[PDB]
Structure formats: C-alpha cells, structure tokens
Amino acid sequence: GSNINKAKVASVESDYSSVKSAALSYYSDTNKIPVTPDGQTGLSVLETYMESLPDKADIGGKYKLIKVGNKLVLQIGTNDEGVTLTEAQSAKLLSDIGENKIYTSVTADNLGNPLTSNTKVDNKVLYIVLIDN
Image 1 (spheres, rainbow, N blue to C red):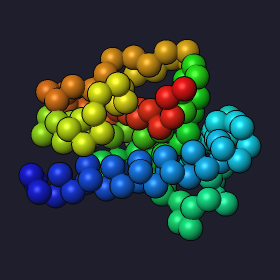
Image 2: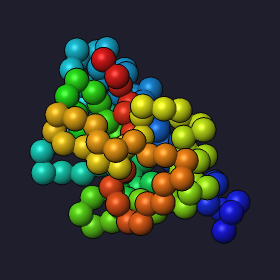
Image 3: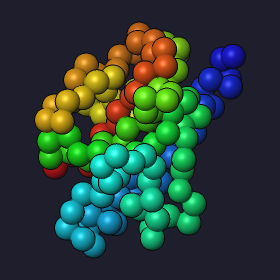
C-alpha cells in the first residue's frame, strides 16, 4: 500500500526528469517542440536522445507528448487506461514537482484544473508541463 504507492509516484518523477532532459535537447537542436504524431501514443519522437524510451507510468497509462498553447506537456494515459492516485500519492507528486505543472484536464489551448494535495484520481488521463515558454 503506502510505501509501494510512494515508489510508483517516484518512478513517474524519474520518467518525467529523463523525458524533460531529452525534450529540451530536441527543442534546442530543431527549434521545435517534440510532439507525438497525431493519432499515435508513445515517445518515439525522442528516440535519438534516449537509450531506453519510457512506455507506461507505474501509476497507470501510456506516455505521449502534446502541445497545449505554447507549452510542451507529458500526457499520462489514453482512452485505454488513465492514472490512479490516492491523496497521499497526489501530495508526494506535488511536493516533488511543485505548482503550475500537474493538471487533471486540458483543451488544445488551455491547462485545466490543477492537481491538489487532496485530489484522488480514479483511472483518468493526467498532464505534466515539461517546457513552459
């Protein structure tokens, strides 16, 4: 329960850090935000920059990269499966990553409701800002 759940959150944080470094490299080299091709999932857009591509989050859900306004966003989950978070998992993720990054909804233009330290997520797609311009 408690310790396993905290380590699943830490695993997403490690994936986030690795993907963020690779994304910044791609952005510096191409002058364009790396995005998953329309109609696909996964991080193969970053394959030149990563020895091993993260596939699924330990909290549930496949990874992909989307543009939301001017921001690069790590999407965690798809139609098939979203993330699951207890309040304690949400609290750790926010303590470690900080504010204005983790969202429970987006449109193509705008970040939606921010995750809070009291939020439970039951099989829903989650969003973490990687690059804020």
